[PDB]
Image (tube, rainbow over all chains, first blue to last red; front, top):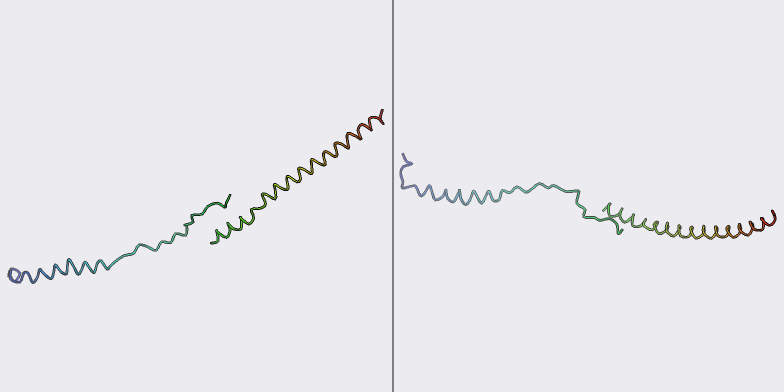
Length: 51
Length: 54
């Protein structure tokens, strides 16, 4: 089994740690879901006329 | 904006309270004056009429 040849094990481990812990995560951080544009038509800090 | 403009309209209508108060003061004074004149007239005429009736 070529999977047991431990000589090429760093070549398979070092890029993965860059791809899984740096690049894919930097691409998920740039995937953002903004909160809904919910517009409140009820917002009026008013008060009775000056009486 | 519409609500604020309506509030301004009511503020513009405010003056009727003081119009009412002034109307009532004037009318009460006039009623009192006329009742006093009728009282003095009635007493004078009433005494003269008691004399004429006896």
